[PDB]
Length: 140
Ligand SMILES: NC(=O)[C@H]1CCC(=O)N(Cc2cccc(Cl)c2)C1
Ligand SMILES: [Zn+2]
Image (cartoon, rainbow, N blue to C red; front, side, top):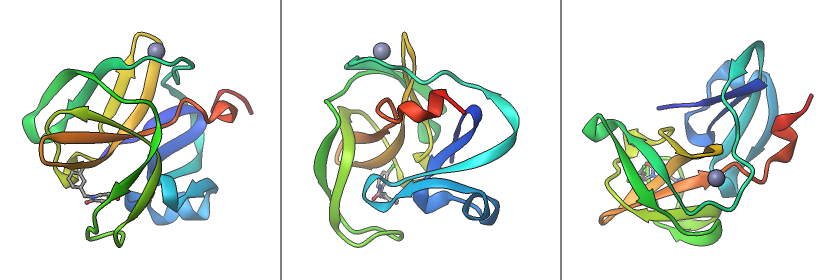
């Protein structure tokens, strides 16, 4: 679990969104495993606007934050799970690191702010859904 709170927005993994999130839906994309809903209170996170390929992510299954190098956001094939059949997931970045399904939502950050959230994993790899291209998250 985990979410990003920027301005009047809440960013979560699409597969973990709540009834309030869908009722207050701003934008969602199944192919990215992302969902954004509106909030009443102002959040305090900053989204990074950069091309960083190094950062730190939180891994709940190890209660640990790990420094990682990660790939550029890309269209990557993702195996079937409890929430999606096998498909291509867009805007996905991989790193060598530990992750388990419940680790989804853990933040990846660089010196500039939040880069994305854990979305995939398996075989010593961890994948993050990028949020740096969602420029509208910085306004209104
Ligand atoms: N983005 C996806 O398709 C997810 C959907 C939910 C989900 O359980 N997975 C599988 C998964 C396996 C290992 C680590 C992680 Cl973080 C996730 C894939
Ligand atoms: Zn950065």
